[PDB]
Image (cartoon, rainbow over all chains, first blue to last red; front, top):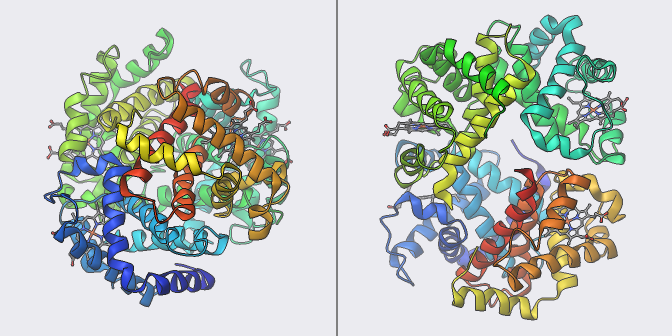
Length: 141
Length: 141
Length: 146
Length: 146
Ligand code: HEM
Ligand code: HEM
Ligand code: HEM
Ligand code: HEM
């Protein structure tokens, strides 16, 4: 599924993400709505009324599921299955959307980390978020 | 790099491709020019004047390099290197073009094979031609 | 799109013999069996998880009839590609956000099954002629993404 | 594209402080270091094969100045996006067939380095505002693919 050095660059990035994880998830969603107008076509039931209590909570959940991906990055095929069963068995959330929010994360991470755009960190976080996508878009298992 | 069953579906397809390999390469190129007009933007030095002596010869070479990929499908990283050194060190041939000609092959193969669109054969030939791309688009090695 | 009259004759006469339910079942089948992002809709198809499941699925054949019936509304009205498909471009965002990358693949895949089903007739320009209508169809469903 | 006046103020004032050579070196660097299809042009850059190679390459910085200088010709003339870029859309096909998938990535990547370089100022709409100009820029270079 993945490589050894990519995990190290993810664990390093996610280590400075720390408690900020939920805020970067929240920002990455708001960013995806603004920076890819097509996601407003999903008819979100959310308010997006600035400072939104639902976006910070969803942000923490997306972030904790990213922590779960970091904790299990070669072992996550079933550990994100409840989130696959969400994005598939409800709403039909296209995995192409994931790439947009993931760009939005990479950007927000770059707003706080040393470079974030190195070969080791950019190739890693693009292909790691791509495997988080691949595993969120698994079948029945 | 790849999977075991994909090789079997490639070897099966390429087995009925046989002597027709060069003609399917030739057709796949002409098809890519017509079906993806952007390749005419490469300013080809070729004539494309029907029955072209250069397209049948290039077709046989593309096809023999596909035979070389089939013969070495997990061992080709350097065996297509002369063709990488072509597509990179000359003309800058974008690997996105490869996907277009590969669709064009899959189509021409389907015009002669039983289904060609099975899960085992379509997933295989899409991801095999994608690895032929990945290996034609290797670095210095 | 706007094909040349000989290209139009080639694509529309291949359409004229086309088995819309079975070329549609096998177009939509051919796409679905790569296990791509369109497999997320496998629950509305009800069968896809195996070759025999997707190829024999009455819902993949029926949905095949709808996607290709619209493709034919294309070949009947190529002067539109902005109004004939607009209800589809709406469906395929305002109710189904589902990314148009998926439409590009269905399109590409359609040309392939036609060349399977009519492999003695699959000429270099007929497949491209198909692709010009198809690239139109994907751009038309994607219009609502302005 | 056609951003709202507050969005325009945000993107163009972030442009107004932008280090065009170093944000350009790091935009083009950020793209090049994923080892994507744009690495096939590494021979014209002359350095890319390592982090220090691409980030310090005078040719990646200089080419960064050209791509982003054109992006600024965008923010100066958003009423065009069809004539200001047309010589580039020509260069980027009629002399460089190089696929516009590559332009979409450079574009996306550009917004990211701006948010690195000005991370205290990288607002949710400023990055999207960038992306609206950028998606315009990629569509403008892709215009010649009609
Ligand atoms: C970075 C990858 C993502 C992760 C890890 C993730 C994680 C989650 C989690 C943990 C939940 C809460 C419910 C549950 O326990 O399953 C959730 C809800 C949701 N997700 Fe995601 N998600 C991701 C990507 C996406 C994408 C691409 C979209 C599309 C815009 C999306 C849209 C939603 C929506 C609409 C909900 C339901 C809101 C609610 O809680 O009522 N997610 N996601
Ligand atoms: C299916 C993958 C492909 C294979 C296996 C392949 C193979 C070859 C081979 C063997 C040659 C002859 C020279 C040599 O020995 O290196 C060649 C020439 C060439 N290829 Fe490809 N090729 C492929 C894809 C492409 C693509 C995507 C294009 C772009 C349209 C392309 C354009 C050319 C051109 C322009 C030449 C030079 C013509 C000449 O022989 O003077 N090739 N290729
Ligand atoms: C690009 C070729 C395609 C065309 C022209 C097309 C056309 C159509 C048509 C004509 C309908 C029915 C319209 C109606 O009842 O008002 C439809 C429905 C639908 N299509 Fe497509 N389609 C295409 C591609 C796709 C793809 C690839 C997907 C999957 C990702 C998709 C998913 C759907 C769904 C889910 C429905 C059912 C919506 C409903 O009525 O509840 N289509 N399509
Ligand atoms: C989407 C953002 C981009 C813009 C706006 C852009 C703009 C430019 C500009 C202004 C020039 C010089 C024009 C001239 O001298 O007449 C140029 C040259 C060039 N660009 Fe881009 N570019 C972009 C993306 C790319 C990408 C991603 C690639 C690589 C795949 C690329 C490859 C080239 C090459 C090879 C040249 C040099 C051609 C020559 O003059 O010999 N550009 N670019």
